[PDB]
Image: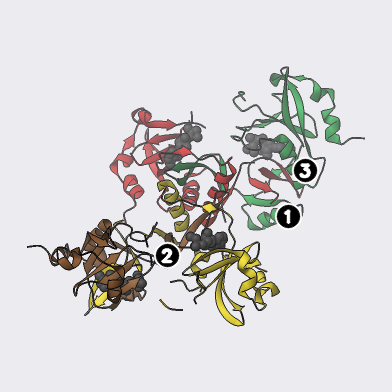
Chain colours: A brown, B yellow, C red, D green
């Protein structure tokens, strides 16, 4: 039998021609990255539309493989194709997790998440800010931006 | 005697600023806010976007710390108070850098920027493979987001 | 975290009693000592000239490690050559190109990196200090940098 | 009336066709840079002919005209050195002429000595830096490495 996520993906609900406004009520998060929607009780879909469409987590296939590894669960997420406003678009589908953000800045919390990840082959790094890189006469400068992460090592 | 504090303490800076007269100084704008070149050596990022809307939900100016760390320069940037149309607003002041974008899609450039930052105690990463940690009934889950870096090292 | 260079040094290969005849094939550098490649990843400066500033491996290794911001970049070590305990300089082998700092842009970037590592950098264009009956004079030489900036 | 150094440079001893064999006795030092000879009681001449008798960015103190400017400033003495043209074996060669200083190396490793020299140079518009070692710069896949060599000075702080 197919995994639960694959069953959702083959469901008529997922394979229908979707209008962005008809799923506004299922929105749960959006940004320059795209928009996240709870389109089933157990799953969310990240649609690449910038309020819309380098960007964060650019290719669903690679993100999906990283999320599957990080959660040690081969059925956590899938890349898939959805029809959005008459157009075929690659989206990221993953298990919906009902819960609250983990405060990974607290140092014990940090170790817990870090050790768990490492045992699954993933190396975690906090993000302090994002910035852009400028070069002036061979010299690098770091300004407020959004192209790389910069965190205290 | 720091050039950045001098500018902040200058009358040009702490007089009641009104948005109309600096519109010609605008160099960039986005959801985050708007950057103006208010001196030949400094820019100021003001939290009004392209539509003039607008601190929770990591872009608080207090950025200064990490920009100063990234650039290894105590006087690169400040969080400061500027009055806009009669309202004291928290802004970010930085040294103006006239340069080109440094492209870190290029392997060599990325390793060069990375090497520099590491000598400054700063970890650098692409913005791909980023995530958030959710906690559901005690258990840690990893989802698509922008709180942490998920790498395979 | 067993440093690769510590592992190579405390290896038998290195601690072997060595003839100059046996390692000639690994010669890559020469001058007034000679640089040999005895591993895939490390080179060794031996003070045998084309037969013998502040060029003491102890000190050079210290400043190479600071300059590269890498505590494992290099070591001073005892190697035995023709029955003689000799102090040698062992550093990470770097397969690369010469980075031209006559180019101003290149110079500045190398300078900004070194500065972030607490290292001052300069061209070799330099003097020596002499004292003559109490009084200091400065002549052409190589002890200090004389700069106007 | 010209400076002592300029009188030496206009002398027949300096202006003659120089044969290296003839001034071997007046030698005082030699290295990769060239060779220093005492050709007058009061003056030395640095000849850009190496210790192997077989001689621009590659060597230290390459431009004698510029080195001379720096030595004059460092000693606060406009007459301390000159660059000049010498005829050596029928060929014109630019050399560095300096006052001969009969003295001992000043040990800059001692901290009081270091600051004495630093303070004196600073009063003269010259900024001193010690030289811990010399190095070469290598680049490998965009990343700079620093190995044992002689192209740049590397010093702490
Ligand atoms: N699989 C998921 N389950 C639950 N929440 C998720 C999932 N993937 C993403 N999110 C949340 O979606 C939101 C994205 O909206 P935003 O805060 O604007 O980035 C964040 O709260 C994420 O933690
Ligand atoms: N300190 C700075 N010096 C120079 N340019 C800057 C500085 N901070 C931000 N910028 C530029 O401001 C612009 C912001 O517009 P945007 O591309 O919409 O983010 C970009 O071109 C940035 O590179
Ligand atoms: N750690 C190192 N990795 C790679 N090349 C090196 C290293 N140390 C020295 N060299 C090279 O070895 C050679 C020795 O210089 P030479 O004495 O002129 O033969 C030069 O080409 C140096 O750049
Ligand atoms: N003007 C000068 N007066 C006295 N000694 C000098 C003068 N210029 C250079 N020297 C010394 O001449 C020596 C020859 O160079 P070398 O022996 O290779 O270091 C060096 O020790 C210099 O310190
Ligand atoms: Mg931009
Ligand atoms: Mg997020
Ligand atoms: Mg000398
Ligand atoms: Mg000498
Ligand atoms: Mg060499």
Residue pointed to by mark 3: D72
Q: Quadrant of the N terminus of chain A?
A: bottom left
Residue pointed to by mark 2: A151
* Residue A48, placed above or below residue B134: above
SS at mark 3? helix
10 Å crowding of disc 3: few (<14), some (14-19), many (20+): some
Front in this rendered view, residue C43 or B151: B151
Q: Position of residue A6 (x, y in %)?
A: 15, 63
10 Å crowding of disc 2: few (<14), some (14-19), many (20+): many
How far is mark 3 from mark 2, CA to CA?
50 Å
- Dot 1 falls on which chain? D
SS at mark 1? helix
Q: Is mark 3 within 8 Å of ligand 4?
A: no
Q: Position of residue A18 (x, y in %)?
A: 25, 66
Residue pointed to by mark 1: D122
Circle 3/circle 2 CB separation < 8 Å: no
Would you identify the image quadrant in which residue C105 lies? Answer: top right
- Dot 2 falls on which chain? A
Would you identify the image quadrant in which residue B145 lies? Answer: bottom left
- Dot 3 falls on which chain? D
Front in this rendered view, residue D8 or A28: A28
Q: Is residue D7 left or right of residue D51?
A: right
SS at mark 2? strand
Tell me, yes or no, if residue A111 can be seen here.
no
Q: Mark 1 or mark 3: which comes first in sequence?
A: 3
Q: Nearer the viewer, mark 1 or mark 2?
A: 2
Q: Nearer the viewer, mark 3 or mark 2?
A: 2
Q: Is residue B126 left or right of residue C129?
A: left
């Amino acid at each position: 039998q197919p995994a639960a996520i694959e069953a959702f993906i083959n469901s008529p609900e997922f394979q229908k021609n979707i209008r962005m406004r008809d799923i506004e009520k299922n929105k749960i998060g959006s940004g320059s990255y795209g928009t996240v929607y709870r389109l089933h009780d157990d799953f969310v879909v990240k649609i690449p539309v910038n309020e819309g469409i380098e960007h964060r987590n650019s290719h669903p296939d690679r993100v999906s493989k990283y999320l599957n590894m990080a959660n040690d669960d081969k059925n956590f997420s899938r890349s898939a194709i959805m029809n959005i406003n008459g157009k075929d678009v690659t989206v990221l589908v993953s298990k919906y997790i009902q819960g609250q953000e983990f405060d990974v800045e607290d140092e014990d919390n940090y170790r817990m998440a870090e050790a768990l990840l490492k045992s699954r082959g993933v190396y975690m790094h906090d993000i302090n800010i994002l910035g852009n890189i400028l070069v002036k006469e061979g010299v690098l400068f770091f300004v407020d931006g959004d192209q790389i992460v910069l965190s205290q090592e």
